[PDB]
């Protein structure tokens, strides 16, 4: 399975922080926002990843993250000229995807919880159908909404319904089989001028293979949409990290724990960073 991080958009609510740059370049506590969804693709076992952003921001992502080699993965880059919808990721990414399965994660989504790595690897290892991830939120009408029965079978999925049929938002992480490319090429813009991921997911519902993994109350799916929520998200990460000795979405750590790089390679990443706490964390990990 390949992975795409869709990381453009407008971030207009965050102005002036986004006057020049895209929101996913901004900090969430101690690392750029985009580290968090990239870490999720990596934990899923995905090592070939395309990052899509605006014409002006795609090079900024590339200057931050590089080509992947030092994390033992492959990062590629492509441009989305206008934010004409999430489903456009599969069109821009058609060549990249080829005949493979592909996961899509949004560059501003932050997932954290016990047992998540197992759920990701399960989804990434499926060879047919779509997996989406549902989360109980206060205001479901603001989101794609997934309705399911007592057995966990999807009944419906609607984009910002007037009268939400459940409390479960569909989060910005999706795993698809290769049918997604031609599905995306065949949907049409919604009223709001967007090629909708909800329409992609409707197509898999109709195909009888839309699977939902319900993230329970013990999971965190953090909002980065406003100044207030961004700050809350930062405080959340700080609190987890302070108590334990452990960082959330430390890319180099994940690359080592996933076996993408060796202990020797980790040591070599840590060395030039030894003046700061991040490098020291990496070296402590190498030492144990
Ligand atoms: C619709 C769309 C979203 N996005 C991404 C960017 C983010 O990672 C995520 C959210 O983007 P948006 O859907 O643009 O929402 P926003 O919160 O960035 O904008 P605003 O504050 O102005 O309401 O989806 C794209 O990259 N391209 C697109 O075509
Ligand atoms: C291993 C690892 C996990 N994570 C994230 C993924 C999940 O959101 C969260 C928990 O990771 P998991 O791998 O799900 O670990 P866990 O809490 O299940 O504990 P264990 O399996 O050790 O009993 O931490 C990182 O950010 N970096 C990492 O190196």
Image (cartoon, helix red, strand yellow):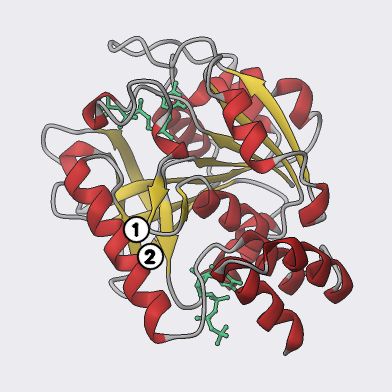
Q: Position of residue 248 (x, y in %)?
A: 49, 67
Is disc 2 placed on a helix, strand or loop?
strand
Q: Is residue 54 above or below residue 18?
A: above
Q: Is residue 46 above or below residue 181?
A: below
Residue 151 visible, this orientation: yes
Mark 2 and mark 1 in contact (Cβ < 8 Å)? yes
Which residue occupies 34% across, 27% down? 18
Q: Position of residue 270 (x, y in %)?
A: 73, 67
Task: Report the side of 83 relative to 14 (left or right).
Answer: right
Specify the quadrant of the image occupied by residue 179: top right
Task: Report the side of 236 relative to 9 (left or right).
Answer: left
Residue 221: give its label. 1
Which residue occupies 64% across, 59% down? 251
**In terms of image quarters, where does ligand 1 lie?**
top left
Q: Nearer the viewer, mark 1 or mark 2?
A: 1
Residue 215: give its label. 2
Which residue occupies 75% across, 31% down? 97
Q: Real-space Cα distance between discs 1 and 2? A: 9 Å
């Amino acid at each position: 399975m390949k992975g795409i991080i869709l990381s453009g958009g407008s971030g207009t609510r965050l102005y002036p922080l986004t006057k020049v740059v895209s929101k996913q370049l901004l900090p969430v506590y101690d690392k750029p926002m985009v580290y968090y969804p990239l870490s999720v693709l990596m934990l899923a076992g995905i090592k070939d990843i395309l990052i899509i952003s605006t014409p002006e921001d795609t090079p900024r992502f590339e200057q931050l993250l590089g080509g992947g080699s030092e994390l033992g993965i492959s990062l590629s880059y492509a441009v989305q000229s206008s934010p004409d919808g999430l489903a456009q990721a599969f069109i821009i990414g058609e060549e990249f995807i080829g005949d493979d399965n592909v996961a899509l994660v949004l560059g501003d989504n932050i997932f954290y919880g016990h047992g998540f790595t197992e759920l990701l690897q399960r989804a990434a290892n499926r060879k047919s159908g779509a997996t989406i991830f549902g989360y109980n939120v206060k205001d479901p009408q603001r989101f794609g909404v997934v309705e399911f029965d007592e057995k966990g079978k999807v009944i419906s999925i609607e984009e910002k319904p007037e009268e939400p049929k459940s409390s479960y938002a569909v989060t910005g992480l999706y795993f698809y089989d290769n049918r997604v490319v031609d599905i995306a090429k065949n949907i049409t813009p919604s009223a709001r001028g967007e090629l909708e991921i909800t329409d992609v997911n409707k197509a898999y519902l109709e195909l009888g293979e839309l699977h939902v993994e319900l993230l329970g109350r013990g999971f965190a799916w953090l909002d980065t949409g406003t100044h207030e929520s961004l700050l809350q998200a930062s405080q959340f990460i700080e609190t987890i990290e302070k108590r334990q000795s452990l960082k959330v979405a430390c890319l180099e750590e994940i690359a080592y724990r996933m076996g993408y790089i060796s202990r020797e390679q980790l040591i070599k990443l840590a060395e030039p960073l030894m003046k700061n706490e991040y490098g020291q964390y990496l070296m402590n990990l190498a030492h144990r």
